[PDB]
């Protein structure tokens, strides 16, 4: 019984620890990207003859 | 008395053309603007 009285402090302390771990990890794994596209043309000379 | 049958090809190297060749009137046709669907492909690729 005395040992099962553990839940009082272990359950919520662990829950909040996992909460802070999640709230830091989600912001820490942002993996930001930036991209752009263009349609620039390429010219190849054609002999006139 | 002669009686026999033969069948011969139309030697498509020499003959066999002389037709419309449906390549044309379709190759000179929209093949360029239809290809120009690169615009739509770029649009979808941007949001992809």
Image: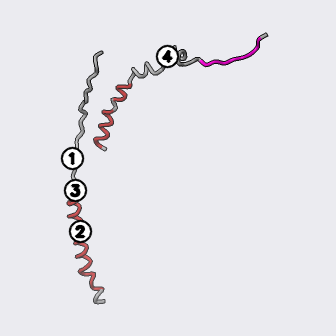
Judging from the image, mark 4 belongs to the subunit labelled: B
Residue B1 belongs to the span the image colors magenta: no
**Residue A30, disc:** 3
Marks 2 and 3 in Cβ contact (< 8 Å): no
Q: Are marks 1 and 3 on the same chain?
A: yes
Residue at the image point whose x is 27% and y is 85% from the top = A5
Q: CA distance from mark 1 to mark 3?
A: 12 Å
Q: Nearer the viewer, residue B35 or A18?
A: B35
Residue B7 belongs to the span the image colors magenta: yes
- Look at the picture and state if A7 lies above or below B29: below
Residue at the image point whose x is 30% and y is 85% from the top = A4
Query: Which residue is situated farthest in the top direction here?
Result: B1
- Look at the picture and state if B47 lies above or below B24: below
**Residue A34, disc:** 1
Residue at the image point whose x is 41% and y is 22% from the top = B27
Q: CA distance from mark 3 to mark 4?
A: 62 Å
Query: How many numbered marks appear?
Result: 4
In this figure, which residue is indicated by the disc labeled 4?
B20
In terms of image quadrants, where is residue B31? top left
In this figure, which residue is indicated by the disc labeled 2?
A19
Q: CA distance from mark 2 to mark 3?
A: 18 Å
Q: Position of residue B46 (x, y in %)?
A: 28, 41
Judging from the image, mark 1 belongs to the subunit labelled: A
Judging from the image, mark 3 belongs to the subunit labelled: A
């Amino acid at each position: 019984s005395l040992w099962l009285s553990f839940r009082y402090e272990i359950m919520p302390l662990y829950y909040q620890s996992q909460d802070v771990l999640d709230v830091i990890a989600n912001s820490t794994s942002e993996f930001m990207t930036s991209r752009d596209f263009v349609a620039k043309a390429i010219n190849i000379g054609i002999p006139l003859e | 008395d002669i009686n026999f049958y033969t069948r011969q090809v139309i030697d498509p190297r020499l003959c066999g053309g002389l037709a419309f060749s449906p390549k044309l009137n379709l190759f000179r046709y929209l093949d360029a603007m239809s290809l120009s669907w690169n615009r739509s492909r770029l649009k979808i690729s941007r949001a992809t």
